Amino acid sequence: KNTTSSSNENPILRWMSIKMNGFQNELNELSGHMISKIIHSQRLILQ
Amino acid sequence: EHIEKFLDGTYQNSIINEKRKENILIGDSNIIESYQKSLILKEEQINEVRLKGEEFITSVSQNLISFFTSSQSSLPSSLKDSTGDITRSNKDSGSPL
Amino acid sequence: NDVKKSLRGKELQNYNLLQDCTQEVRQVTQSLFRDAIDRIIKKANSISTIPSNNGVTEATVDTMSRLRKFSEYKNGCLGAMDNITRENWLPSNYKEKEYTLQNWEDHNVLLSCFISDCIDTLAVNLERKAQIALMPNQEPDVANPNSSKNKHKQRIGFFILMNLTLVEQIVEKSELNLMLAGEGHSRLERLKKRYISYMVSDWRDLTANLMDSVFIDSSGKKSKDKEQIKEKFRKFNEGFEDLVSKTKQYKLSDPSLKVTLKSEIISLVMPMYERFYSRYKDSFKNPRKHIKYTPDELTTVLNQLVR
Image (cartoon, rainbow over all chains, first blue to last red; front, side):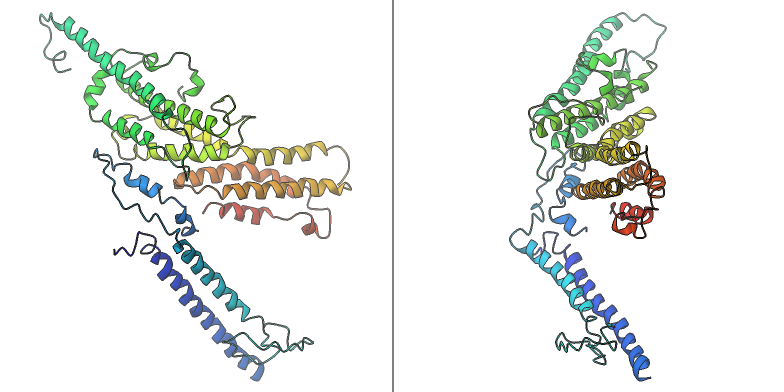
């Protein structure tokens, strides 16, 4: 139309871009703590 | 919670917002292409499909802490799910992690 | 108003006829106010079903924007409140328990009196319509949180309190806002607390037969009848999660209603489980396998029952 949308995809880019923030943030956080934990595994097993 | 609380989640009370006429003034001329009806043709299933995106991504996320890392250093286990080496005994490790 | 006030201490002789055709324009007020009440009756009873997502019939929107048409004739409303009864807008076979109303002094009395009585009429007619439309074979029994009849006190409660959500959210910025001071706020509060208590009803069943389950086995010993442990505590968990389950059907709109129903039902439940949990938490090495919640975690459940 566009609209793009009908709130609910513009305002569910409040979902979609922010579900992309839950996803990109999820990879961010798991990336962080996983990276530092494995860093504390070469610390914790090798070192 | 809110995003599920907009699908059926009224989203008609939002139509009741300007359908208070914003009185004053007197109209009541609400011709919004109402609204965001919406989504029943599979875009609701695109929404719940995205929620499967989320809980799925958490499922593979913590499911990466199922291997310990399979017993041992597969430590950089960032990707991906495979290799069920089933030497369960012993410590070093069922741990994960 | 301008002419009968105009300048006095003088001969004024058509002033009687001013009071007579002005007595007919107070039959235009009077007829417009019995028209207001009967307007609520017929214009409300127009609809027959609670809505799809159970919202607000826009006959109520008509009723409140109808009231803001009663608003900005304000000073003519003030003089228009002259010398006329509450029963000059009443279908006389009413009861006053229908009306959250508890003087005869000025027109500011009949201001909040009259308008808040009109929203009481909105309450009794909407309430009647729900009482019909859910149990379509019964007598509509009204204003009754202690009803032994309704099965939909939560549902009717959220319906009606969305109607009042509308009403105070037009008295939000109205002149009625600045008109109906003092009592009429508290009239609206009692109006709320009815349907609030409708949404506390089966929680009062849970607490009711919980502490009754304390009462009937308050006779004998410590619970070697461990069917009483898992009776009170299991069935308490059963009805508790039933109530949390049917709490999920409704999602509130006033934040102060969230605070209201929240702290109400917290204050309903808690001390029972405090003295009762803490009374009977001495029965196993794992009460866990029989008794589930703390008051800490149950409190937390209630505090995220109200997202």
